[PDB]
Each structure stands twice: as C-alpha cells, then as structure tokens.
Length: 124
Length: 124
Image (cartoon, rainbow over all chains, first blue to last red; front, side):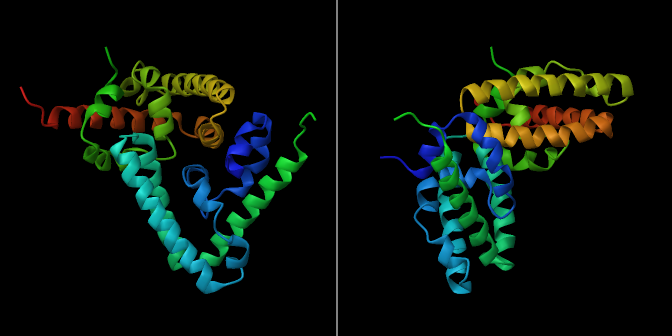
C-alpha cells in the first residue's frame, strides 16, 4: 500500500537521471518526497487550467510545507530545515506570481513518473 | 569524539537561522553535512590566499563528492542523488572559475560556527 513515489523508489537508480529536468524552482524534490502523499492527492492537471484552483492548491502546499518545517525542526534535521526555508521563500514568490505554472510543472512531473513506471522492466 | 558539525547539531535549532547566508553556490549544506569530517580537515584559511592550494582542495572536494554520490546511489537516496549531481555541476563551474573564493566561503562558514558554538548558552 504505497504511493507512486514509493513505487519510483523501487526502480533501478538509473531512472533518476530522466526526471532531473522535471524539477525546477516551481517544484523541488524535497517537496515531492516529504509530501509525496499530499502531492499525489491533488488534481494538478485541472488546476493547471484554473487560476482559482491553482492558487488554492499552492496556498495549501505552503500550509503543508510549514507542518513539514515544524517536524524537521523537532527532529533537528539541519539540512532539511535549511533547504525547506529557502524553498518556502521561492514558493511564496510563485504564489504572488503564477500559481498555474506550478500546477503545470507538478502535473508534468507526476505524468512523467507514470510513463517511467510503465516503461520499467519487471519480470512476470 | 565528534566533529564541529556534530557539536552544531547539539545546539538549539534556533541558531540555524544565523548561518543561512554562509551557504551559497560556492558551498551548500549538503556538502557541509555529508563531508563534515573531510571539510574540517582542510586548511581553507590558508587556501583562501593561495591559488594552487585552493585548486587542489576543490579538486579533492570533487573527488569526495563522487564517493558520496556512489554511496547515496547504492542507498537509493533519491533526494540526495538528485541534489548532489546538481551541486557537482555548480562546483565544476567554480573549479573553472575561482577556487579561492570557494575556500573563502568555507573558511568563513567554519569560523562562524566556532563563534556560534562559543556563544551558545550551556550550563556548567
């Protein structure tokens, strides 16, 4: 009973090179990983053509990001606290700029994983 | 028998906010953490005024970074593999540009930690 991210984690590490360009300022892997289940729950595809929806999703992403920051702070995970706060600043800027584009990037990233998962060689 | 990094990890999490500006493209926290002992072994302070030394240190940092990449690949730590490869590209550019400046940044970062460690309130 795993997420799409959990399925990606079971693939041979060589696939990872194919997804590099699907992550940029609009969507970093820290978010993909720490919030995998939340990310996989939203309809990014519909939000990518709807201003109001995209804004709501980004607002909620920011709220989840803060919860993550509280958790890694309690865990004293220095690297993640440091990286997450820088990500938060970038995402705040996306909120004031173009939330729909963030939805586009996440939507592409998730579909790319579906493509890769289907392509992966697996024995019957 | 811990490193300066290990000592920083024992501080109250609020200190972390003070070191943010000491990390930039020339030196990311991923390197500070994964290679804490190696970082703490080099004489960055002397390399910051010596071209040849700074170049040698950066070449060796790149060699250690590759070993780290082999380890996280074996461990299948997606986030770190992804982040480390992007860091490697940036550092390669620093090697062709200004290695002395990388030494300056690391030297400042380590001294800043010494300042913070000394300032930290600790009961006798």
